[PDB]
Image: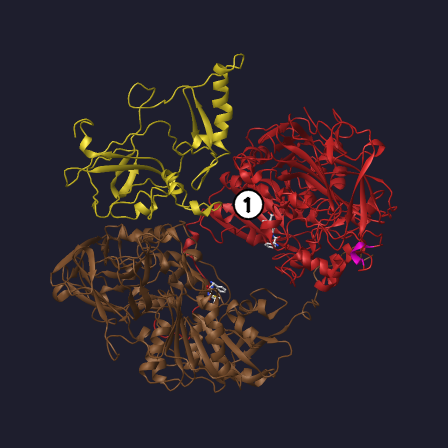
Chain colours: A brown, B red, C yellow
């Protein structure tokens, strides 16, 4: 029979060898790199055509290396095939490497969520540190087009693997750039913020741990997660209905609600500081990092306190989580001066890496910190940062006290007073307007810059503000909440927001008129007031002292603006509700545990609530 | 060691026992259904919880059955889990079945693009007809929750499987509804339109035939496919560079550019009419179906001509390809009276199926055709349709003649004349505004309703129009292009557009003022003027007679509007360029073959070019 | 299904709601015009209009009621059907035998925004469709009390004038009482995801308490 007319076989070719591969400006190599224990990791190596003695940029990920190196699947150019954040390195003729971490996608082995370093939580012979070590060693001995020099980078979990590598790096690892890294999931990164549980973790658990490869989110009943979580009750109740009780990582998390040995043995900022790395580091996070706000700044500061003898620079731009690898010209309704993300990548990131990865390159002398000013709209270069803080700094912090008539003053109010608000767990304050589902990435990403006017309009939120500013107030450093608060219950969460109120009218951009822009906010779970590792019941109606750091600022409250402070006791559904009655484990709270409570914030006198502001000249 | 602290194993559970399955209102059964030759087909059966004596709605697809039955992956309700087009059947308590056709995704066997029916092109013991027969037989003997009655539906390729089943159906198949079915890929469906090749097929080939499962599109050099295809030259040159020469189906298509035995043996409209089927049929296609305009109407008409002894109704709504399964409220800038798609599904589709699938249900008496009026904005029920055509109809067609001064008249112009335009293959007319890539689904879907003013402004397009209408002109049926055209070359394509010019000003919706809306347009490859199977060279400068049907219409050209006709010789990059020089195979046209030509359209006299309009009272 | 003066524009939508075609043009063309032609253009066809022509915001069609309404408090074919507030913040057609009460604190320093902040009366685009806005923001507040039926197994048809029969107490000596009748959309609306659980008010109003006994004498 004529094959050009009659097909009795298959129309699917046995093997494909398309000439589009010869039309590429790069070469893609797939290799199973063996670790010291025999476990092989899937590694993608993207080499520019005619590359000779080129440096290597490495990233280790739980997010499918094959896909990460395929922004535009099988693209004709390296620029399209690699992520937007790799732009400056593609332009620099770097060799790009993406590797699936142990137990994920193309890699063999067992997967352990944020696998702990060797120690009491990991008694085996391998960890993310040795895996990175073995990887770098293989690369410098099996990539002839390379110069044997490796640089490491990555954001979030991809930043976590960089930090792990820094614990004991291979001699060929010449430079590192952890971006929004997961450093302490309990203190202020992905899982908790000062012990307050982040409910978006459930979808992440099922999505990343259902299979070696891809997984799905938890099927929902309602389009609104405010509804879904409130109806389920406690976080543990939602997890149980989702089937998470059979997931080993959730089993461990549920067993360790407090900051005990399980979480302390995973605090990478403290562990890295003990090791005192000698590899040049560039730490980065967004000023509005909605997923890993604790990581970079705390790791960088710990290293500074440990007196590291290696380049250790902190970079913070006007970005959301991982925004550094995309376009940084805007965030929500905010507009910045140009693509700040590309600016950093091109003017700082790239030259810094070139110095150690490309022999003969110009030397860069980076300061302590490079931070974008969200007030002046420009990049600030700080030789020594911060210049103001609570201890061991040139100057101290400047308290902005809460006052009578819901005001704020830099003068300590002698008059004693208190403002009350009722916190009702049956009607928790939406962290962003309803309806909201964790699946709505477009709403989640810029949530930290949203207008706080909705919250202000509620009786379960207390708001304070200065008079309209006649002179600008410059802040640069870490604000500290010095809170004196009472609750009629035996437990409570305390949400503190530092806000920049835009001019009453903004005629050049009308929508921004009176807009309440939060520059720094966080939540503190009251039971941990005395000890993060040992939760304790609060005394009903007792004015108690809470003292905790808030996200860093580098802002200028300009003329016409106001400084504002908002305090509330819920932030739903991002954070699970504090039942306001002391229970052993808030994950297991029952319907009858949730108690309406009256909260009282004291102002003036010996218990003068204030925000310790890093005011500078 | 403590397992709740120390994990030396994997965080990925061996298997998941999700309790969310008990909250579902449906169950899913996955079965490998064996065909008569031993080959097993992956079949997904979606049964409403506690269903009994329920009818079955079956669809056979090359687009992943598992995914088709997972609109919202693992949803809690059957309504979410199934496609939007299944809404009325979910409400009716139907059992939904999606099956992977032989050789695709979860199914075994060899895959053959639009596998031809048993005959000269398929000498084996199986085909899509027997596969459907074996499937229905298994379903009625292995699904206890069913009443033994099966209904078949599906759009495009999923409609093609319905037609194939109708060739020799199982006695349990009580009713069928082919939607925009692939019936004749050469005459006017997916691959060609009157011999003019559709270049979007290349991406489809690589996406559907690279592997049993999912594939990818062809990597592009430029963002604009106008640029990509023009730079490549001929369609065969693009296919070669894409690596399609190793794909068996392309090898067969390339060897059969003309309507020979290979395509004639695949014309389902002619084959089905010869089989004398007795299964009630409901044929559907969009009035603006940009992918399968030929299929439904031609199959329905052939059966009507063969005096089919079964219900045979044609339905055409104001939809784009497969629009019947979504929301039919709008299309491009057009707005219709409500969700026309849901209206049809609820008022016609569902009750028709219920009559034969749910014993005891009310009987429906559908007319010849149910067509939406794109002028009156209402559903028309035509007992006998069409009422006007070339032969064997109640009335004849009404010619709208091209006239002097670029006008259009219902009066046969006595004066002989001609208008000329230069067709340059180096500057082909964009079918839609540049830039355009076949990957841009949002621009491709509603392309048939786009404003034709851009084309009008070009010197390589001739435009004719009536005076502003003082009285409405109603049309219902199939328009026929009666073209008398000459070319200075030895080959040429002829694009003819029937347009409704909106009122000069539309104050209630300003953007529509003077908008040139095409209600019916198509292309004809000149070499097939005398015979579709035997291409012939055209005589240079000879006025030749072209006679071909255009897409059906059911419209009213209202007062203030104009009727317009546009003629051109290219439609890029949707259709490959006619070199305008007769070559044996246009697929393999060489750079030197492409020739600039002068086109002349004659009007009036014995060669009075016109559009034979189906004008009705 | 229109906002104020919506009859003179396009009636295909209102906020996020979508109706069956341009309902405003439908009325203007099929009812308004022929009715006027009968008395203004001698020789025109006579039209026999019913008591009321009302669009059904549930069935998405025009209803022609010869006699409307068919149910009301006095002098109608039938009476009204009470939908009682119940324990557990529920709603029931069955009169609850036991006495109960739910409380909420009304603070004038933090009044409930009728629509999301910020809002200026100059923003006509936000003002026009305000009556169809989602009431989920209000529900989330402690100064708002919310009641709901279980998910409906059977449709409930309503046509006429609803009446608020309120038994309320305040610790003050005056108070406003806002009552909203809402249709909660299905938990999930896969064909239009944004509508899932949407709390659409079909009828709401406010009553100034001082006028409880007499509108003329507070
Ligand atoms: C590094 C990223 C590009 S991938 C990661 C991500 N996406 C997901 O987590 C998503 N569920 C996913 C995608 C692919 C495989 C597995 C899971 C996202 O966002 N993060 C980015 C970031 O931090 O910049
Ligand atoms: C029936 C459909 C829902 S799937 C089909 C489609 N999409 C593709 O062809 C696409 N390449 C694809 C998607 C998923 C798996 C494999 C291939 C599209 O559009 N058609 C729809 C229609 O006709 O209604």
Magenta range is B585-589
Name the secondary structure under disc 1.
Answer: strand
Q: Which residue is at a point 45% across and 47% down the rendered structure image?
A: C193
Left or right: where does residue B186 sit relative to residue A66? Answer: right
Check the picture and name the quadrant holding the C terminus of chain A.
bottom left
Residue B543, quarter of picture: top right
Pointer 1 local density, CA inside 10 Å: few below 14, some 14–19, many at least 20: many
Q: Position of residue B580 (x, y in %)?
A: 81, 51
Asked whether C56 or C113 is in front, the reply is C113
Up/down of A229 relative to B354, above or below:
below
Residue at image x 82%, y 31%?
Answer: B415
Q: Is B614 on the left-hand or right-hand side of C218?
A: right
Where does the image place residue A536, in percent across and percent down from the top left? Answer: 20, 67
In the rendered image, the vertical position of residue A228 relative to residue B504, given as above or below = below
Q: Quadrant of the N terminus of chain A?
A: bottom right
Q: Foreground: B413 or B262?
A: B413
Residue A282 vertical placement versus B399 (above, below): below
């Amino acid at each position: 029979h004529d094959p050009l007319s009659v097909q009795t076989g298959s129309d699917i070719p046995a093997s494909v060898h398309m000439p589009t591969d010869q039309q590429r400006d790069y070469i893609k190599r797939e290799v199973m790199v063996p670790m010291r224990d025999g476990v092989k990791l899937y590694t993608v190596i993207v080499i520019p055509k005619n590359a000779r003695n080129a440096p290597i940029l490495l990233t280790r990920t739980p997010y499918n290396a094959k896909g990460r190196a395929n922004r535009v699947p099988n693209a004709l150019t390296m620029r399209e095939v690699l992520p937007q954040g790799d732009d400056v390195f593609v332009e620099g003729g770097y060799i790009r490497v993406f590797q699936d971490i142990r137990g994920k996608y193309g890699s063999q082995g067992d997967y352990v969520m944020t696998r702990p370093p060797h120690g009491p939580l990991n008694p085996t012979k391998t960890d993310e540190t040795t895996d990175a070590w073995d990887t770098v060693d293989w690369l410098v001995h099996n990539v002839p087009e390379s110069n044997g020099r490796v640089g490491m980078t990555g954001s979030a979990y991809e930043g976590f693997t960089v930090v792990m590598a820094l614990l004991d790096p291979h001699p060929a690892l010449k430079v590192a750039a952890p971006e929004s890294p997961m450093v302490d999931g309990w203190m202020g990164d992905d899982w908790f913020h000062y012990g307050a549980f982040r409910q978006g973790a459930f979808d992440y658990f099922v999505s990343q741990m259902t299979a070696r490869g891809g997984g799905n989110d938890i099927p929902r009943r309602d389009a609104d997660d405010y509804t879904n979580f409130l109806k389920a009750g406690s976080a543990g109740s939602f997890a149980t209905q989702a089937g998470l009780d059979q997931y080993p990582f959730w089993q461990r998390m549920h067993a360790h609600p407090a900051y005990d040995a399980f979480w302390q043995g995973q605090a990478l900022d403290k562990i890295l500081a003990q090791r005192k790395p000698t590899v040049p580091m560039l730490w980065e996070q967004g000023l509005w990092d909605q997923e890993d706000m604790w990581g970079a700044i705390h790791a960088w500061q710990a290293l500074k306190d440990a007196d590291v003898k290696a380049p250790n620079t902190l970079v913070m731009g006007p970005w959301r989580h991982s925004g550094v690898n995309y376009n940084g010209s805007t965030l929500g309704p905010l507009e910045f001066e140009g693509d700040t993300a590309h600016q950093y990548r091109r003017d700082v990131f790239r030259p810094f890496f070139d110095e150690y990865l490309k022999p003969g390159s110009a030397s860069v002398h980076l300061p302590d910190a490079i931070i974008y000013n969200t007030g002046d709209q420009k990049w600030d270069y700080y030789r020594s940062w911060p210049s103001v803080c609570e201890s061991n700094c040139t100057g101290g912090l400047t308290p902005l006290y809460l006052a009578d008539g819901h005001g704020l003053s830099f003068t300590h109010p002698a008059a004693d007073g208190a403002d009350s608000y009722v916190s009702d767990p049956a009607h928790p304050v939406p962290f962003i307007s309803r309806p909201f589902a964790f699946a709505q990435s477009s709403r989640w990403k810029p949530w930290l810059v949203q207008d706080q006017r909705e919250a202000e309009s509620r009786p379960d939120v207390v708001t304070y503000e200065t008079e309209v500013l006649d002179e600008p107030v410059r802040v640069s450093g870490v604000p500290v909440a010095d809170l004196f608060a009472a609750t009629s219950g035996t437990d409570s969460d305390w949400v503190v927001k530092l806000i920049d109120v835009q001019p009453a009218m903004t005629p050049d951009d009308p929508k921004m008129g009176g807009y309440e822009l939060p520059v720094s906010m966080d939540i503190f779970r009251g039971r941990y007031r005395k000890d993060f590792a040992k939760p304790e019941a609060l005394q009903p109606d007792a004015t108690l002292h809470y003292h905790f750091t808030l996200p860093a600022v580098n802002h200028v409250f300009a003329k016409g603006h106001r400084i504002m402070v908002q305090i509330q006791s819920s932030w739903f559904p991002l954070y699970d509700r504090n039942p306001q009655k002391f229970v052993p484990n808030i994950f297991d709270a029952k319907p009858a545990d949730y108690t309406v409570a009256t909260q009282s914030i004291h102002h003036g006198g010996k218990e003068a609530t204030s925000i310790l502001l890093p005011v500078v000249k």
